[PDB]
Amino acid sequence: SNAMRGYYDEISFDVNTTAKKMHLFLMRSIASYDVTPEQWSVLEGIEANEPISQKEIALWTKKDTPTVNRIVDVLLRKELIVREIRRISLLSLTDKGRKETTELRDIVEASCEKMFAGVTRTDLEQFTAILKNISTNIE
Amino acid sequence: SNAMRGYYDEISFDVNTTAKKMHLFLMRSIASYDVTPEQWSVLEGIEANEPISQKEIALWTKKDTPTVNRIVDVLLRKELIVREIRRISLLSLTDKGRKETTELRDIVEASCEKMFAGVTRTDLEQFTAILKNISTNIE
Image (cartoon, rainbow over all chains, first blue to last red; front, top):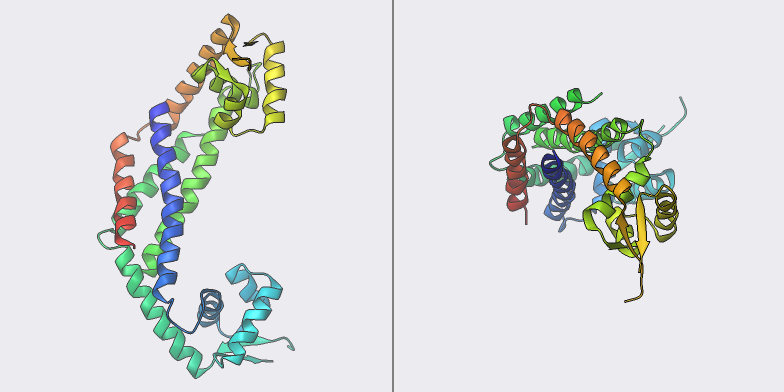
């Protein structure tokens, strides 16, 4: 199936390029807000896990120690998070952080709905099944 | 659609991991033959394009000049290809090269059919349509 291999290859290229464009689209939706994309990554991670250690945020966001330290410092200065004291340091949201994260999450969610307009869970599970078929076929 | 984004993300991971496994599977099918995987890449490219320049084989296979030069030298020594003389150098198959490439292509094709057993062109075009939908939705 030289032909089928061709069609699959087009799909692998398209899945990856579309994934990249989807991320850009969601980031464009909050472009006008005071919180930047990298600040949002950290804020979102804190909201999802609070109270959470600076070590664990790095793992969650896949950013290095220095990068997370830098962004956490900006978020503290913006009064969006608080850093409190075993004797290691945990991050959590302030009232202002909770307000802003809620506002941003809602905007991102609305754009995400637009992105998936006309696509159903079933549409996706059908292709996951094809990948399972191929995976089974091969040993 | 936090949920839908989750399902899509699982698909992007699975498409890429499955692609890698498919390549390994096809390479396993010819593991016992005298021609190695990297030699096959070059041989296949020559068969598909002969007579073809050493420069163009590099582009076709996405290998660098030194790598292609090395592999071409092995294929010349194995008497599978011939290098002949504007005044630049073109590669083509010998009778032995044509015989061996035909044998290998047939084995790979048979394994490729096994890989795609129960998967139809239609199954793939339906997901390409979903990617087009998402791509359209976003601007």
